[PDB]
């Protein structure tokens, strides 16, 4: 459906401020000015054959799930610029670093559920993300996270997030996405530690072949670490399925203290109904499955 992608002229938007720079391009806070109107509407803009580009943009614009960000519009000039909904809380990687040791188990486990729900939706569509990482998950509210940057990897190298077969053979599948999910979970549980820090990307493949993996995060029980380890099995078909991961983390979220050990966790519960309602009226009106609370 081409009605899902708005083609914008550069005259009706302007980049105002940089939010982050990558290898794919630069992300700006921006403003949309509807033609014939006076209002400035805050948006996010990412500046990176047109037919090949538009073909993929239409796919990205078709993504409709509470946990994957949808491409809303595009402007093609000398540059390709993408427009999506601005999310003030930013990327989850920054969020966990800036809130280190101050995040409750209920939030961490529920984020794992939500990311796996978003990836399952892509898998059902037979779509592969290719670049899942904490830097590519955004916070809509503390209770609601969303995968972003879908489509860009294919459209345009994260060795330390990649499945061995991706490193060696540039094979990308749903099951290589599961490997990167495991690394993403590791990032969250360590509050944004760098994976294999101090180790050259050039030797990651040899480290993995020797059976070495990312270490157990200090807050993870053995059951949680075992899920991560299963995500990094050499045999792709022996790794978990996103559908299974949804179920597993949803179970842990029902008894969160049994699965993560976090100091002061008893005062880091999910927000009250009052506060959850305020957050939603104010910045999260889209429909979404209820978060999993403790039994």
Image (cartoon, helix red, strand yellow):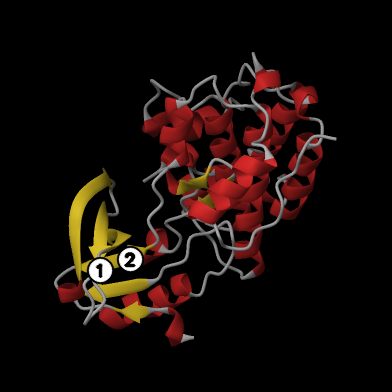
**Residue 154 occupies quadrant:** bottom left
Q: In the picture provided, is 256 more to the left or to the right than 115? A: right
Q: Nearer the viewer, residue 107 or 261?
A: 107
Element type where label 1 sits in the image: loop
Q: Position of residue 294 (x, y in %)?
A: 80, 34
* Residue at the image point whose x is 65% and y is 15% from the top: 264
Q: Position of residue 223 (x, y in %)?
A: 77, 28
Q: Position of residue 271 (x, y in %)?
A: 64, 36
Answer whether residue 282 is visible to the viewer in this image. yes
- Residue 126's place in the image compared with 190, above or below, is below
- Residue 161's place in the image compared with 33, above or below, is above
Count up the numbered dots: 2
Q: Position of residue 160 (x, y in %)?
A: 45, 36
Which quarter of the image is occupied by the C terminus? top right
* Residue at the image point whose x is 69% and y is 27% from the top: 225
Answer whether residue 48 is visible to the viewer in this image. no
Of labels 2 and 1, the one closer to you: 1
Between the C-alphas of marks 2 and 1, the distance is 17 Å
Q: In the picture provided, is 156 more to the left or to the right than 204? A: left
Q: Nearer the viewer, residue 120 or 164?
A: 120
* Residue at the image point whose x is 59% and y is 21% from the top: 215
Q: Classify mark 2: residues with Cα within 10 Å, few (<14), some (14-19) or many (20+).
A: many
Residue 39: mark: 1
Element type where label 2 sits in the image: strand
Q: Nearer the viewer, residue 208 or 75?
A: 75
Q: In the picture provided, is 274 more to the left or to the right than 82? A: right
Residue 83: mark: 2
């Amino acid at each position: 459906n081409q009605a899902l992608l708005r083609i914008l002229k550069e005259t009706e938007f302007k980049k105002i401020k940089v939010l982050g720079s990558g290898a794919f391009g630069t992300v700006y806070k921006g403003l949309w000015i509807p033609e014939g109107e006076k209002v400035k509407i805050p948006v996010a803009i990412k500046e990176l054959a047109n037919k090949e580009i538009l073909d993929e943009a239409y796919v990205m614009a078709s993504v409709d799930n509470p946990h994957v960000c949808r491409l809303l519009g595009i402007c093609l000039t000398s540059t390709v610029q993408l427009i999506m909904q601005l999310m003030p809380f930013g990327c989850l990687l920054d969020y966990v670093r800036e809130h280190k040791d101050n995040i409750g188990s209920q939030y961490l486990l529920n984020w794992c559920v939500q990311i796996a729900k978003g990836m399952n939706y892509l898998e059902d569509r037979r779509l592969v993300h290719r670049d899942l990482a904490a830097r590519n998950v955004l916070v809509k509210t503390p209770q609601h996270v969303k995968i972003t940057d879908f489509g860009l990897a294919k459209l345009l190298v994260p060795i330390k997030w990649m499945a061995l077969e991706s490193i060696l053979h540039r094979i990308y599948t749903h099951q290589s996405d599961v490997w990167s999910y495991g690394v993403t979970v590791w990032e969250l549980m360590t509050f944004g530690s760098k994976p294999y820090d101090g180790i050259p990307a050039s030797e990651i493949s040899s480290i993995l072949e020797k059976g070495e993996r990312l270490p157990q995060p200090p807050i993870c029980t053995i059951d949680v670490y075992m899920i991560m380890v299963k995500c990094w099995m050499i045999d792709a078909d022996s790794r978990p399925k996103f559908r299974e991961l949804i179920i597993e983390f949803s179970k842990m979220a029902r008894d969160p203290q049994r699965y993560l050990v976090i100091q002061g966790d008893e005062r880091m519960h999910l927000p009250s109904p009052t506060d959850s309602n305020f957050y939603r009226a104010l910045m999260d009106e889209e429909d979404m499955d209820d978060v999993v609370d403790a039994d």
